[PDB]
Figure 1 (spheres, rainbow, N blue to C red):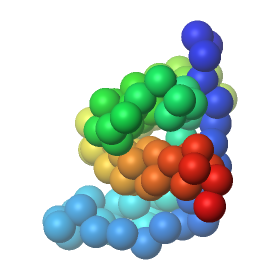
Figure 2: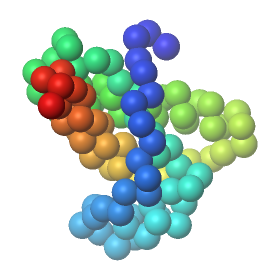
Figure 3: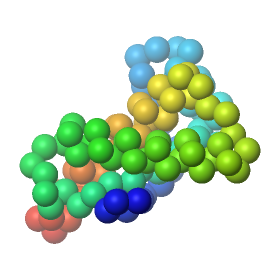
Figure 4: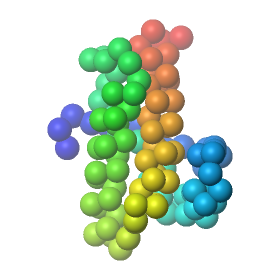
Length: 104
């Protein structure tokens, strides 16, 4: 890949975009969707959003390719779904991996 690691699968998180059409598309397709996240160690970072930018990138990059070959067809919609859940889970796993950096 280049140096990334699938952290965990989120257990159908239940979250809000702020939208309706997005909210629903997650909770109708989340079973098919990438609901895990790939990352580097937080060990060469200090902030969430930029690690998270790498994180959601490699997540979706692997998945979009692989899942397509397995049979799938995401859209800029399914993307903005994935991209949301995966970014909030990337940021949240940074919090987890940071707790584990400190190891509390």
